[PDB]
Image 1 (cartoon, rainbow over the protein chains, first blue to last red):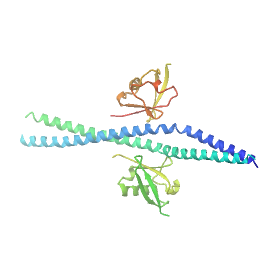
Image 2: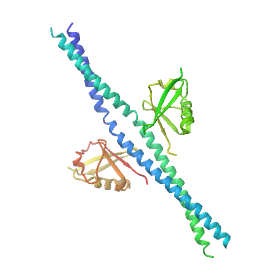
Image 3: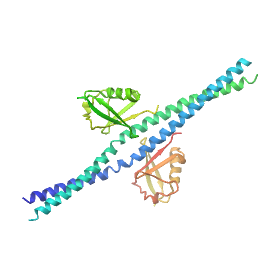
Image 4: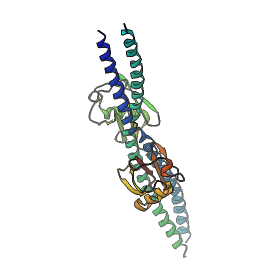
Length: 75
Length: 75
Length: 76
Length: 76
């Protein structure tokens, strides 16, 4: 009658041990999260820098196309 | 006689399992984003590179224009 | 029966969608496009670390209303 | 004393560096620069989910031969 409680208390113990096992095994993969976030942030910031640089070169391109066109007519 | 100390120790043990299961639920949520973050990184990388290209091509045309403008200012 | 799913982004944004379990992933990606304007050929969907296939169905992946789905897409 | 550490890039590459525990983080980055051509001022080194300061030492972070080190960087 009491030994069912003693062999349940053991069942509960290896459920606690097995949870602490896996919890240590996946704090390893959980410490790549911040690494993955930083890599994504760098590629995002880099992309935005390339986009702003492209828009600036667009402004200049179209500004030069004018000067060229006028001074071609002029001469 | 000490069946209600085993029963109450069974209870105390489940109160720990519940806390760990709860911590392992929150761990699981983080870990399933890892493949998502990998994919995010890969796409942003391809976004960056694709934008460096479009902007390099636009940087060439802008020099060609600036070279065509200065050659015809020899007149 | 017609159920509500929730597609979350890494920034913490959530897109609610009304879907039928028989719906394909392309189908779900079409809904996401009609709502936030992201071309389907540019969305990637995740469930339980798995990358979801245009061709398979929510039924196939066993997606319920309480399901944690993730969306990644291009900055372009 | 004189030991081998391994730095995991997210592109899969493992960079093997011979270092001393007293080697400073800008020193590791210079070694990485010599092997991979990534400028130091553009490398981020990680260990136990934290970024490593250019001015502290491998031994200030208790970094061993088995320690899991990640390198993240810019392509600009």
